[PDB]
Amino acid sequence: APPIMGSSVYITVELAIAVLAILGNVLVCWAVWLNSNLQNVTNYFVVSLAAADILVGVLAIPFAITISTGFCAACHGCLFIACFVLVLAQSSIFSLLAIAIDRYIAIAIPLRYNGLVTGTRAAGIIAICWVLSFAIGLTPMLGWNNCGQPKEGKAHSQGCGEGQVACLFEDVVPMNYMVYFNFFACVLVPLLLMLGVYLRIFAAARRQLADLEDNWETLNDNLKVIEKAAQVKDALTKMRAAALDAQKKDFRHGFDILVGQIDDALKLANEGKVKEAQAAAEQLKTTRNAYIQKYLERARSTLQKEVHAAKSAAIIAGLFALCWLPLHIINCFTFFCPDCSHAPLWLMYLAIVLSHTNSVVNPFIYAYRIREFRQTFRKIIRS
Ligand SMILES: CC(C)CCC[C@@H](C)[C@H]1CC[C@H]2[C@@H]3CC=C4C[C@@H](O)CC[C@]4(C)[C@H]3CC[C@]12C
Ligand SMILES: CC(C)CCC[C@@H](C)[C@H]1CC[C@H]2[C@@H]3CC=C4C[C@@H](O)CC[C@]4(C)[C@H]3CC[C@]12C
Ligand SMILES: CC(C)CCC[C@@H](C)[C@H]1CC[C@H]2[C@@H]3CC=C4C[C@@H](O)CC[C@]4(C)[C@H]3CC[C@]12C
Ligand SMILES: CCn1c(=O)c2c(nc(/C=C\c3ccc(O)c(O)c3)n2C)n(CC)c1=O
Ligand SMILES: CCCCCCCC/C=C\CCCCCCCC(=O)O
Ligand SMILES: CCCCCCCC/C=C\CCCCCCCC(=O)O
Ligand code: NA
Image (cartoon, rainbow, N blue to C red):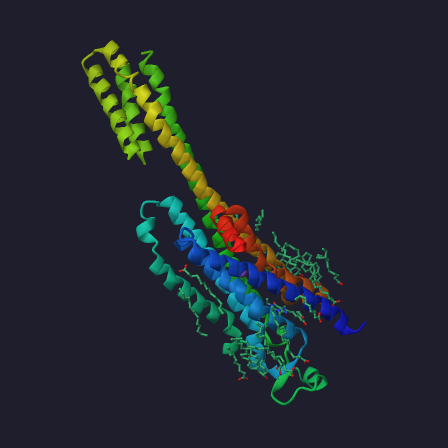
């Protein structure tokens, strides 16, 4: 069949993807500018991520359509066209990595976060990443390419002038750079690092919840042994150690009557007044229900709020890896198996449009998983 027929379908799908990539991600940057609640260090990385997805539809996708024609051009002008999308992919990887680290510091060392992670330092970190992404993505232009061994039979058949070449990715971009340098070092290694950071995040949160529950059960279980008891001095000692262990306002009050009531009943045991030491220790049961019980339930909800946020960010990085791995696996076959038959053009088309689809999914996740984004999105849509 005519080659223009199948080309029109691929061009149509690519042009539609760019429209959704530009529209949705601009809506993300608009919400962060208006709503001040969205103006935190974690969201400055998702705006840098949205800018990379906006630039995919404005530049990378139009570049991909020009590559498909095999037009004649200077080999270095062809290099910038074929390799610019690598600059945007590296920027997203660093943005995903930075997001995972931010949520780790928030759950591991929550007290120092506001002093550790500041808005003026992230603006330089984002700038450092974008400059480094241009270096990684444009590495073939520094000499690691195939401009010195041009395909003349393809250049003569295409009618290319002197100094030009049939602009094709697999012709000017070496496949050892794509597999060893791009996929392994710059993509796979940071992705595995992202998997490790999220493991330590979910485990630490599961341990903090378990530590809080046991500190509550130690406060309750030992309340039954003082009332059914030197035996009262033992439990009142496990009282305090577990009371301050759970200390990690109205709460600061409630702990003061708690540690105070346990202190009063403690000395009543050192001098033998057992029945009075008992009676002085069932009055702290009222303080437990009116103050210490409320602090524990509030911290459990706050813990879930941070975990839900860590889950949402973990989904974004997972969707990235799913949309980009099929393309890299196909390159591993072209490189590691020369006796294999090269992947057909339709499968390559499917791998290109699948990698482009990652520039559309992220604004959907924020609206579905982050309430503040969804509400802010509605105010702009209504107005
Ligand atoms: C602000 C935005 C839109 C700027 C966009 C700049 C783009 C469109 C420009 C900048 C550099 C340009 C390339 C530079 C060199 C060559 C080699 C030549 O033989 C064919 C054109 C080609 C391949 C150019 C295509 C267009 C190009 C990629
Ligand atoms: C990345 C996750 C979702 C797994 C997806 C599976 C993909 C990447 C796998 C499954 C089957 C694979 C194909 C199986 C056989 C061949 C024939 C060979 O001559 C070229 C590679 C090619 C065409 C493979 C390319 C990669 C492939 C399409
Ligand atoms: C951390 C995980 C996701 C890494 C993914 C593993 C990658 C690197 C693995 C999985 C499947 C592998 C391919 C499976 C089959 C073949 C055919 C063989 O004739 C050459 C090697 C080749 C082409 C392998 C190359 C490496 C490969 C692509
Ligand atoms: C993300 C990196 N990357 C690649 O890894 C790649 C590639 N193009 C090929 C393969 C050739 C090919 C693909 C589509 C076509 O229309 C065509 O005419 C030829 N590869 C292996 N693109 C260009 C779209 C690309 O940017
Ligand atoms: C929403 C994104 C809109 C993008 C609009 C631009 C899309 C088309 C871009 C340039 C097409 C490539 C130009 C190459 C000239 C023809 C090549 C040839 O005939 O040999
Ligand atoms: C939704 C289905 C779209 C079409 C299939 C998408 C991906 C299929 C996965 C791999 C199947 C193997 C494809 C290889 C084609 C034949 C290879 C050959 O001709 O030697
Ligand atoms: Na992206």
